[PDB]
Amino acid sequence: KTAVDSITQKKFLCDRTLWRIPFSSNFMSMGALTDLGQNLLYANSAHALD
Amino acid sequence: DATDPAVRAALQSQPSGLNSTDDWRQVMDRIMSLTARNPDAFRQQPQANRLSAILEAVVPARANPTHEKVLAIVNALAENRAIRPDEAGLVYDALLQRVARYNSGNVQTNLDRLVGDVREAVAQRERAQQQGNLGSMVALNAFLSTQPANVPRGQEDYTNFVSALRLMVTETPQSEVYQSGPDYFFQTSRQGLQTVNLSQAFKNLQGLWGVRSLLTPNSRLLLLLIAPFTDSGSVSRDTYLGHLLTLYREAIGQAHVDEHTFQEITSVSRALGQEDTGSLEATLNYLL
Image 1: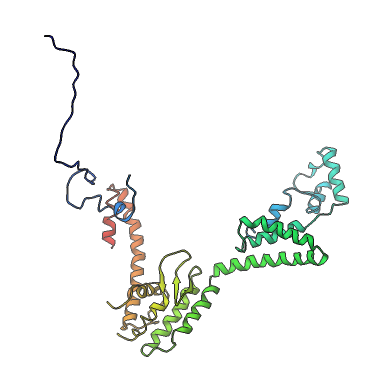
Image 2: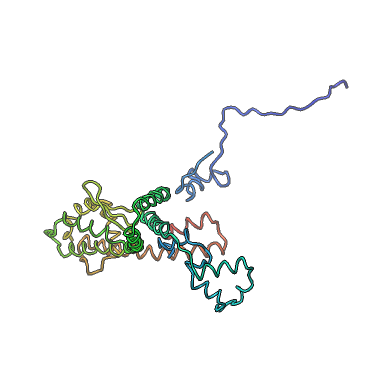
């Protein structure tokens, strides 16, 4: 009954892992050679990555 | 006329209106009101504008052609790449200073001969660009002096190949041959790719003219460029070089109709509704 006014601190810990961002058009593993790695945009042209 | 060094000198030195010295007849047609369009446009001027044009007509003013004669010469030197466009004001004051130190009746006549001489020399260069032959025929015939005129086997294939070799440099004004050290080369266009090595190709084709995995890829690049300038009877049918020249003519004709097939399939794949990424990859894998 004598609880103080409180705020909630939320966080997460995700150890042992690597934050995967797959270079696919729907972020899914439909194969090791993705659909955007075979793309003529990304396989014939040279792009800058920033 | 846009590339005429004296028409361009008239657009930079002569007035843009009708003075009574350069255009005496065209202003006397207007003073005397015998003009077709608006004859009475001269009566409707004030006396300051109307009497000052009558005085310049019945006794006209003399002028210096020297700044106009020199500027026709400078604008032809800047056009035939003899000077830079940044040096166009430097050499204009340098030439005006020389024809001021040495001014004579001989020199002003000699500038009048030289502004007709640079009208010709600008047009002679622009004809020689669109013909595109004089820099290449003297350097391809200089190449063929080095190559022997008598191969042991297949001389009939060899003398028609080198005659078709003269047909590329003649019937393509952008193509050129030159030398860079020992070897000679052939670019199919100015500042373009597909540069074959003539001294390496003719030391590769020598020994293959009558043979009936062994070709350097610049020799095959030469046999691709020489293919539309070679008839079916220019080389043999069973000879391995003649068998490829027919095979490269079919490859050009198939790539000319796969070009038109590409423009049809991708046009009706957008309107029918497909992925624009996959319409452009499934078409090439159907055509290649």
